[PDB]
Image (cartoon, grey):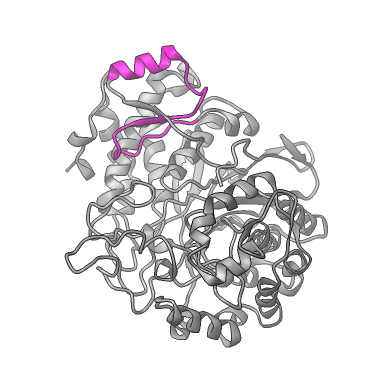
Amino acid sequence: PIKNTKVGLALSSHPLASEIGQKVLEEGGNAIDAAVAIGFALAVVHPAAGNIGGGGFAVIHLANGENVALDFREKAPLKATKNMFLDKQGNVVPKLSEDGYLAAGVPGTVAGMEAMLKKYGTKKLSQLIDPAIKLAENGYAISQRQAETLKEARERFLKYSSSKKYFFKKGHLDYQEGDLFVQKDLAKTLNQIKTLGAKGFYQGQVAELIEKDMKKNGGIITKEDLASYNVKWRKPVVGSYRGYKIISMSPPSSGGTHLIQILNVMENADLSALGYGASKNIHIAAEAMRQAYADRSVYMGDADFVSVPVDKLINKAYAKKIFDTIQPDTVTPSSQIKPGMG
Amino acid sequence: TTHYSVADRWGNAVSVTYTINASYGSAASIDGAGFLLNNEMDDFSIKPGNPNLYGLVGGDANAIEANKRPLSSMSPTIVLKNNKVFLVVGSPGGSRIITTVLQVISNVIDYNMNISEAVSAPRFHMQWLPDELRIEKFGMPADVKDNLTKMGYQIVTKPVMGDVNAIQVLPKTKGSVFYGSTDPRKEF
């Protein structure tokens, strides 16, 4: 593996972003400092996934023993409605939820980065964001993988004048491997955030740009949406597995809950006995997965709006019930699964 | 989606998964601002029983409402041993995130893999609907596949799942050693 015995590690899917996070550690920043620098770096160098136009979660273990979760997940706009993606006849409008301006929730990433920095960081945002800004203004080399993913997204980009301007070379030509990709408008936006903090994204000129481009293009995100965007510091979901404490993301993610649920079921077997890749072990895990995902489809959503029985789903007694239905050499077909098992 | 993991000398750990959902989000950017818009709305159930981009289904609980946050599968996770940081782990992959992350954790805990081994090891996936056992190329030999098919799994080989960036922390006489793995898969 990668190794460090002094300042720790900051690891991402892009070497430029990892290097930026690692430097923050080398220069005396803490884990939250490095994570903020990485979150902005990846918004520049990994635009397939890294972002300021999306959202996410952070699970944090603090030096003092505290465990916290940060929800900076996108919100449905104020104008969002239950059937907004359906037609007259109550049928799904193909790609309405996937391609273009109506598919977007109110972005949370910038608020999320500032929130964690203000509460737990030690370095100024102004400094942590400079490496991202430099990469946007000066550019970076399109990688082999990026050339592939950009190629695949071509016909999607082509639908929107704004994306054709940002993600193609002149004449709407694909960036190729090794090309220098410069993002001047993105640097303008990051520079607003550098100077003004998150209000640089959620208010003022960038908010105006967002609101007016939404309206032009059939989206519904307004200045009111942006000014009302709120992160939420939430309790993580916590479980145990064979003497280890599991700390993961609670609603509005289902991930941490079902992670703990599935492991709870698996805990009833001595998996170590047969070892990695044994069909008997794969069967126990897969059956646990099967029940968890059935459960997910009925019980899971934003707990601010619906009742989510997290405590019941992570209860070891529930997991033991699941485990006891598992047959040595046959499955419970998915059609026979009952969410919650009654 | 993309996941990143950070751990420092003072004992803080930060595990972040964040996203614009699909590869390049909604594919639409904000004119004048230079950034792509998420298509996170597809993480809601847009019609009961309708499968989204990851084959995930829903009803009331994950219905769209004003201001509501769409249901996620993201699983940034920290594992503690004796209250000290042990693993910092997460992955992208929509519905596959939960199963990717649990397999990495199980590989370390149940099988005593180091973090590099834990991350590289082939991954399987069951998400109830579709009713299939998803595996990776070269990941399961004939003997295992035949035994699982006999139990009644429908096995399918599909593109590799996830892109785990994980840290393992181990105590040393003075301080700690930090071990890392990136994922040889790069899904996104």
Q: Is residue B142 highlighted in magenta?
A: yes
Relative to A297, residue A45 above or below: below
At horizontal 41% and vertical 23% (from top left) the residue drawn is A281
Residue A246, how many percent across, how many down? 49, 45
Tell whether position A296 is magenta. Answer: no
Q: Residue furthest right?
A: A27
Relative to A232, say whether A45 is above or below. Answer: above
Residue B118 locus on image (x, y percent): 58, 31
For the question of whether residue A100 can be seen, the reply is yes
Extreme-front residue of the structure: A171
The part of the image, by quadrant, that contains residue A81 is bottom left
Give percent across and percent down for residue A26.
82, 55
Residue A212: horizontal and vertical position, in percent? 49, 84
Specify the segment rendered in magenta. Answer: B123-151
Task: State the residue at coordinates (62%, 71%).
Answer: B34
- Report the residue that reaches farthest toward the top: B143
- From the viewer's perspective, is A25 left or right of A262? right
Residue sitting nearer the eye, A242 or B120: B120
Taking A314 as reference, is A1 above or below it?
above
